[PDB]
Image (tube, rainbow over all chains, first blue to last red; front, side, top):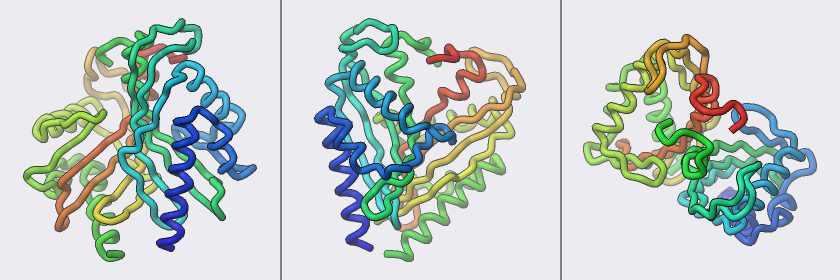
Length: 139
Length: 139
């Protein structure tokens, strides 16, 4: 059990290191073939999920995951993460602004036999949308 | 230690039930007098944090906290929560639309001797802003 918590946490920290080296392979290798992704209490198709990830790296090619807290109980792990980056790539049809941006995410992962079978996210990207002029500054 | 995790979880579920009857006293009584609130990696003054909570209830007087997951390790607890409500009170720039809204929050709480000494939140209210048309539907 203590062993289980520690090894699941070490897997999440490999996945963070993979994001930080910008190689989605180091992330996706930990996913079960039938992994389920949830965002906003809806299923996200795995293909859609990988396109979101590739889209993010492209817009924010220097992105860095700062793990503020990590927690494990039973087969789940939870990370509270602050992301910092520069807007150096296209972000949808928005041409690079080279502005420094930061936003906040929580990822909940469920492991069976060291594979991610379920993944839930809560992403606050409002601070980044504001800095890029994609939303009004007062919302 | 297993007993601490179980008691800290129950305190958090009692706070969620106080939100759900809109009685902020049933939340605040679990806080240390010198509790520190963090939002987007910024310290929020405790009395400010309460005015923010009062503001939410006024804009959304039927708001309901649905706990999707709860986890505990050491002296901390994390809750992943879906909020639902009707827009019946004025909301910043906007007058009541009576539209049903949903958004998503993660709360992380640190307890010493059964009192909250530290509180971090990550709130995605982008879905609610879209529903009230305060931001483009596509953003």
